[PDB]
Image (cartoon, rainbow over all chains, first blue to last red; front, side):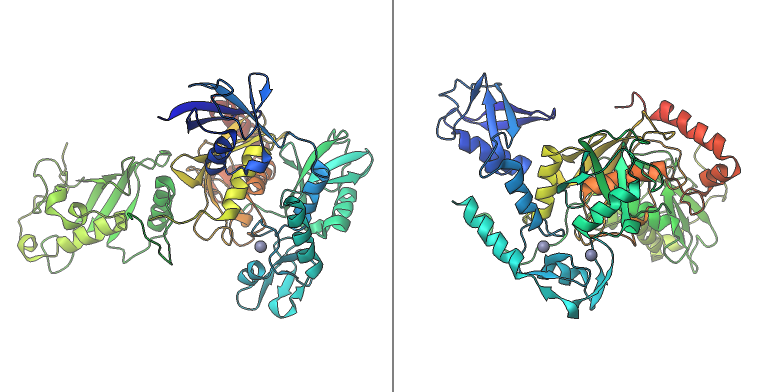
Length: 160
Length: 76
Length: 149
Length: 153
Ligand SMILES: [Zn+2]
Ligand SMILES: [Zn+2]
């Protein structure tokens, strides 16, 4: 039997979830991922002066119907360093697909994209750079393998 | 002084400026870090599109003020 | 199971307002032959609900030279639900209640078997092509210039 | 029937909820993840200051290779905005970049409010007034802002 609870963000947004007393805290973070797009790694749930652990249930924490939870985003402060490790993912993020680079290549201006992402932009042999609008030709695509090695390094870091 | 600047993808970068430094002065530091020419940069603060002439304190940009970067645009 | 894998998926869900904004632009751009025209009744209605259409009578018919103004209303379920259609200029055509201008969606296929692929332009173009048919091509018409109220 | 929403749209939606921009609000519709309901604040030091302007935004099937569709849902006095809220802005057409996002599109729209262009207009009747007497047009934009864009949420 599903029940309703509320998860309010510090921004002001309130979320309504259909949950069960037997749901673990990680089950709720998955329901938050499907509805809000936020991955479970970046979720820290709060209820009644306690931080909640993924292995325990809503019933363990006396979370009944119409209970209000507080969602905090990336509350914790480090995996190496919170903000700095985040900056490393952003440097290897494709500006087009917003995912980590897949076969990263550079164009004339020096900006780098996924090979397939920039190839779609330059259908016909060329276009303008999405970041700086300088003209580029697909024949001058240049592999940027250090960015790809950086992606796997960070992916290994994520899974320890 | 220190200012945050949110780039096109959303990545935030820190910069070294002065209250007296012009807007194009900030664009140069953005160009060195991000490779966007100043003529294609548009910096937004409080919704108003900053003109290259004036200074940071002409817009009351204190420290840890977050600017937002946008591409060159024109109404038509 | 109830669902199966499909390799290709196209046609995202376009909100009602943006579908209506597209139909507004085509009517403003004069797209088509010129025998039909469509647009908003009040150009401040942000809901894009109340529309007004035009239809020129076809040649080789009884409606030749006759300009017909129409009013169309796209409800909150458009373009899934069909729109209400009406006639501003009094007319004699099979499938329309004779003292109203309201269109019997039953007696017109485009509104009876309604799709989401159908636009207001088609409801007007096929209504003029419906007026081309044999039965109403020889129907007697009232004095042009008289309307309902 | 159903297909996966593109990851870029998932990412943009999650970062609109996690890192909001001051003066800009964007929220997806419950029935359509490509449909966004927007409120932007009028730019400082403009006749639109203090106003809250409602917009709706749609991500078409070709996004981000194509620009988002966006229009005002609030009446506004602007030469590049017609009376139904449609906007003529170059980054929404020929000057679109797939590196632009909902966040930077909305920031560019309020940048358009701070830089109206009556020389290349969408609403020619509004622009003719902006060119005849710009001081009166700015006052009218300020009056329209209080009439339609205050206490409207
Ligand atoms: Zn990519
Ligand atoms: Zn570039």
